[PDB]
Structure formats: C-alpha cells, structure tokens
Length: 61
Length: 99
Length: 65
Image (cartoon, rainbow over all chains, first blue to last red; front, side):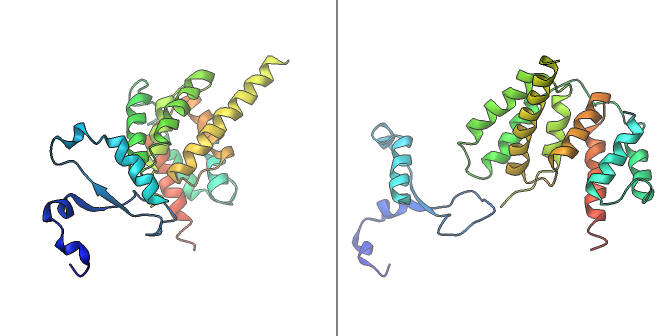
C-alpha cells in the first residue's frame, strides 16, 4: 500500500502471497521465507509447477 | 540373552546406573515388557514408512523423502532385521519435530 | 570365518542407516542401545512396550535434574 505497487492491478497482487519453509531445528526467518505465485486460471498450461520451483530457487539466491 | 536381562542393559544405557544399583525402574520395565512380549501383528514396515514420510514432509525436506525409500530398502537388503515393523514403530513413536 | 564377519560389517551398515534415521527424527538413542533393541526384537517384543519403557526411563532422568 505504501509503495509504487499500489497502482498495479489487485488481481496480480492478490495472486502473489506469502509462504514459508517447513521447520528445522535451526530456523531463522532469513532461512525460512518465500513468496508463492500460484495458478488461478488456464495459465498452468503456460506455467508449470517446476517452473515456479526454479523461480523460487533463484528467488532464494 | 534372556528377555529379562536385556532390559537391564537398556537401563544401563539410558541411566548411568547398573542393574545392582537401581531396581525400581527395572521393576516397572519388567512389568511392562513381560506379558506383552508378542508383536501386535506380522510385519508392515511399509505402513509405518508412509508415516515416517509424513514426518519428513513436515520439514520441507523432500530430497530426504527421496532418500528414505533407498534407506528403507537397505533394511530388507541385509535381512538381519526380523521385525522391521517394530523398530520403525519404535522410532516413529519417539518422533519429535526438530522444529 | 570370513563371511561371518562381513555380515557383522553389514549389521554396522544398517546401524548407520538407522543412525541417520535417528537424527532426522531427533531421538536420543545411540548405536549400542539400538543394537540392544535389535536383540530385543530378535526375541520378540512390542515396540509399544519398549517405547513405554524408554518414555519412563528418559523422563526419570528429568526428575533428578
């Protein structure tokens, strides 16, 4: 809301939402955090789930 | 080795006491273990393995979930384990989340 | 005997397999004690009874802490 993202469509901010990493005995939030963009239409035919995995790996880096 | 005497080695491993030091813990051990000396059914280590997978799922370790199918195979590959169901039930009962 | 000792190496190999299984599950058990448990199920035993035994014994070391 405070940043420039507010003047972008509510749909595509709505499809991006938070996620975490399932726990481990040395948890830091800097170890444990992710964003998930998930499919909401026929776009699964365009965007595979393993493509979101490579997305999240380069996001981790 | 007798059924009775192997629990005192269990008592000497968990506690730092001998069988000639404590007999109160060992008494409840003999009470619980004896008369319950028979497995509940024949082996189903597969059913317990699919619940150890549910513990590996709880940690987003899905690469170790693919290691577990090859670690569960080595138990059968050597064949020194008679009750593969029991020791996996025993480990799974003591499961804590590393968390 | 030579083949009777390679089986003992095989016992240690599965014991290290169960070592990895014990750490990813966070059990307090070590290798000697699990070999005692292996001999216990050679004679036949409830794992539900062994877990009650160890679930009494470990939290009777937390009563003299």
